[PDB]
Length: 184
Image 1 (tube, rainbow, N blue to C red):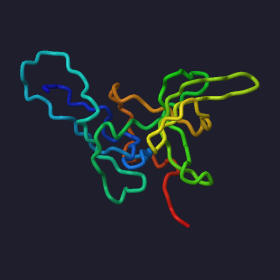
Image 2: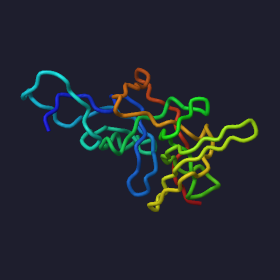
Image 3: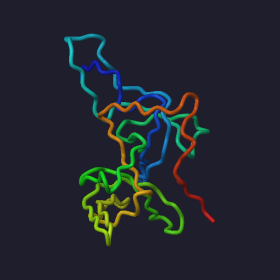
Image 4: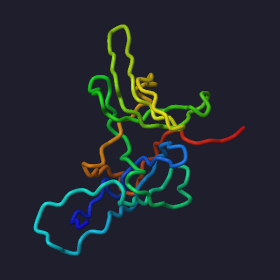
């Protein structure tokens, strides 16, 4: 399809979280170079250009465990902007998609961050329960499950806004999660 918008969903030198393929686990990354779907070389156009869907934009990203492998290109559906703004109980709204630390693999250690749709909120002076639809790896969705804690929860930022969340000049974010798998 013909399109004028050269700008992708995320900007260059942005901190972004990329989701995995075989388990679906969110590993954090840093994009150095963004490549949007081919844009028209001027054909029946005048004004008004729109963002492109999440299939055809490649982000050259460096994985937290794989900076030695340089960068790898990822389709826009496999990446979402790294959570900076954490939305607490005070600004909590039903339907917002957030990530939370869930250790399904070994409940002793920090597992992986998975995305979850916030379904319910119960905040009283005596009890604070937060419920959401947890996406399981075995192709299952556990609706109204107990959300771990707000400091394990980060609010996943929107792509359609065309995010300009840039890392400091010559300084990518050193701060990370605890993510990985190592056998005794």
